[PDB]
Image (cartoon, coloured by chain):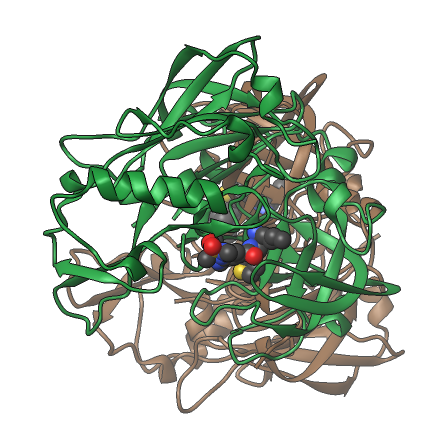
Chain colours: A green, B brown
């Protein structure tokens, strides 16, 4: 019992619906806040004024090391947006690397549908690249500052445990996964973009041109709840899923995420729902691998109706007009390694993923897939 | 409710008999250890090999940032000694300042009567000056490294709570004391040396030449349990204390610290013991102030004989042949500010000191004391 990165294990709290967060200490004297881990954006920002949904916030006048950049910043997401003021300050991650850096920080002064009631986080850590940072790519993202200012290796890994988790910074911890790690190339450094080459529902190929799977783009986003799919792919996926779970019928609104379906405590018939496999481009020509998720991943729990014996679920696969988004529900079945140094993302079966005695999430390979380059949108 | 240094409040654990300690994280990846706060020495050192009394230790091969200085180091104390190897590594204090520095660190490989069974600490943080560091004054002490490498103000304060406490680094927290802070000059920067100019037992002057009080030297040491006094002063003090507590008699060994005396749970007659006042040189010519401690300070508790209703106490004033040592039992009644920047030490009544409904520890002034300069040993 030891593990070199042991102190970083279990440093995350939260859920797929409201977000996973890590503690970060900013300023001097110390001001610790809960920050959302978001690989789908690139700005580090913290609530800096009272808000109905915030238990605490960043108080710049109390930080002797805060430096005002005299520049406003506005960041819109798929869900919500906020306005703030830019500056820099000292930042450390108590349960992360043993270093302290001066990073850019956006003080959130106003917001619309950004903070989530009961989520317990007051800020957001955009872990993606400079290309998508606001106001522009000149605002160095936090991780870039970390790598340039310290000896911390240019890599971090995430293990999101559904119904906390771990964010290993600078390395990987072997106790967080089983089996082998399979890597897919980071196609371009802006979002953590990847390429999906095949999709199966219970082993059955969806039979869509792979270009549709990445139409526009496909990204790995810890800061988005669902597995979002382009319109045409969503429709085909839902039709196949319905056909594979015909043992029981559900309203159309369920598949659209507008209706919830509940079962008596501990009675959900996981067996009636199919597994979904996403094949990703590998690191060798014409070679791919696949990650398989269970209904325990794409059917997410929602607070009991009346604190009784009722497990309510929302279909966590939804439509998108901006490409595929492999969100938290997808990541919850695996240990995901964001190997920025080698421009690749690794996947391995998570040591904490939710499963049963009949099926488990899986990462298998290799498979033979030709013309994978053509799958990408230009 | 806020307090700028609020995150540092309550960052200490421990007791006067075994020591007060703070968490410190060393190396990369993070290795957190419990470290003894010692203002009576100047070396930062941590157990680096298994030991019967250690729950954990520093593993250098696991730290990528460790740098070997290829130099041995030996440090003897009044109580115990250890041998080790010098090097440097990254060091942060989780509940201290929001910075990380590269400091000298001694890896303890062998020791004799140093570590204390059940103390829960695995290292020691020497907070005194370079002059008394080992091997010599060229080995920069931790706090000096902190001040030179960061913007942290050159000052720290201690509130030791007897039967944890707080170590505020870079400032003072007003919630830790009541009344005013009175300062005494740091005579010379090696140990935290001060000058005692008068001593009273229940308001009665001990009537000894003040040179005897600082014969050799007088220091403030958070890493020593008792109030240690030069032989002649100890003898006079004990004689006066005995006379002032004549309502009940105790064996000679008690006053020598060789015998313990116990009372039924919650029955100790604190009222029969006198208060002790130490007058310290002030910051203005011919002006002094005094700190007064209660028997609750100089009579320290010792683990119940058989986990029952018996409060056992050991007389915490003892003899010394190396000058006066104002140890933890003395500090426990006050908030002590080690103002290195202004070469002075402040004292204020602690918001946590142990007292009763009849008496309280006190810090009062000013008083008129002539020829205080002559009190110091040359
Ligand atoms: C331009 C793209 C921005 C992508 C960033 N990842 C941004 C970060 C953010 C903003 C507000 S909370 C988190 N995320 C979202 O916009 C975002 C957050 C969440 N659900 C809340 C997420 C915390 C839990 C993981 N859900 C969605 N969906 C559309 S969903 C229901 O999953 O189909 C989108
Ligand atoms: C050359 C002077 C060195 C002074 C350093 N402060 C050094 C640090 C240290 C070493 C081993 S444990 C702590 N302290 C001691 O030598 C030391 C530690 C403790 N008791 C244990 C102390 C932790 C509790 C406060 N007691 C004493 N006394 C003689 S006593 C019973 O109070 O009369 C001395």
Q: Position of residue B37 (x, y in %)?
A: 58, 50
* The N terminus of chain B, quarter of image: bottom right
Residue B172 in the image: state x and y as whole percent: 69, 70
Left or right, A361 with respect to A67, comes to left
- Residue at position x 76%, y 86% in the image: B367
Vertical order, A220 against B225 (above or below): above
Image position, residue A182 (x, y; %): 46, 19
Q: Residue at x 74, y 57 (%)?
A: A105
The image position of residue A224, as x and y in percent, is 50, 51
Frontmost residue, B64 versus A42: A42
Instruction: Residue A34: tell me if it is visible.
Output: no
Instruction: Tell me the residue at 28%/41% (across/down).
Output: A241
**Front-lying residue, B369 or A52:** A52
> Residue shown at 60%/57% (left/top)?
A124
| A50 lies above or below B372 | below
- Left/right of residue B135 with respect to residue B115 in the rendered view: right
Picture quadrant of residue B343: bottom right
Pick out the residue farthest to the bottom.
B358
Q: B378 above or below B359? A: above
The correct choice, above or below, for B164 with respect to B149 in the image is: below
Could one spot residue A340 in this view of the protein?
A: yes
Q: Quadrant of residue A376 in the image?
A: top right
The image quarter containing residue B97 is bottom right
């Amino acid at each position: 019992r030891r593990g070199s990165f042991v102190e970083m294990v279990d440093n995350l709290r939260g859920k797929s619906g409201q977000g996973y967060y890590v503690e970060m200490t900013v300023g001097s004297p110390p001001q610790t806040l809960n920050i959302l881990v978001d690989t789908g954006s690139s700005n580090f920002a913290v609530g800096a004024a009272p808000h109905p949904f915030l238990h605490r916030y960043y108080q710049r006048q109390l930080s002797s090391t805060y430096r005002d950049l005299r520049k406003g910043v506005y960041v819109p997401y798929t869900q919500g947006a906020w306005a703030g003021e830019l500056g820099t300050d000292l930042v450390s991650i108590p349960h992360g690397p043993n270093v302290t850096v001066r990073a850019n920080i956006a003080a959130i002064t106003e917001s619309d549908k950004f903070f989530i009631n009961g989520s317990n986080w007051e800020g957001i850590l955009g872990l993606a690249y400079a290309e998508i940072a606001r106001p522009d790519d000149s605002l160095e993202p936090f991780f870039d500052s970390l790598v340039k200012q310290t000896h911390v290796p240019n890599l971090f890994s995430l293990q999101l445990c559904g119904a906390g988790g771990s964010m290993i910074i600078g390395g990987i911890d072997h106790s967080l996964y089983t089996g082998s790690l399979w890597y897919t190339p980071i196609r371009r450094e802006w979002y953590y973009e990847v390429i999906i080459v095949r999709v199966e529902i219970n082993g059955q190929d969806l039979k869509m041109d792979c270009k549709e799977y990445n139409y526009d783009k496909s990204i790995v986003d810890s800061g988005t709840t669902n597995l979002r799919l382009p319109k045409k792919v969503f429709e085909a996926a839902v039709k196949s899923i319905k056909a594979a779970s015909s043992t029981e019928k559900f309203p159309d609104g369920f598949w659209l995420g507008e209706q919830l379906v509940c079962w008596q405590a501990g009675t959900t018939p996981w067996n009636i729902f199919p597994v979904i496999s996403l094949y990703l481009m590998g690191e060798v020509t014409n070679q791919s691998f696949r990650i398989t998720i269970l209904p325990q991943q794409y059917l997410r729990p929602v607070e009991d109706v009346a604190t009784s014996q009722d497990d309510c679920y929302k279909f966590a696969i939804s439509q998108s007009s901006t490409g595929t988004v492999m969100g938290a529900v997808i990541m919850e079945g695996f240990y995901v390694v964001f190997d920025r140094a080698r421009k690749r993302i690794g996947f391995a079966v998570s040591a904490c993923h939710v499963h049963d005695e009949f099926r488990t999430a899986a990462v298998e390979g290799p498979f033979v897939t030709l013309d994978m380059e053509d799958c990408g949108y230009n």
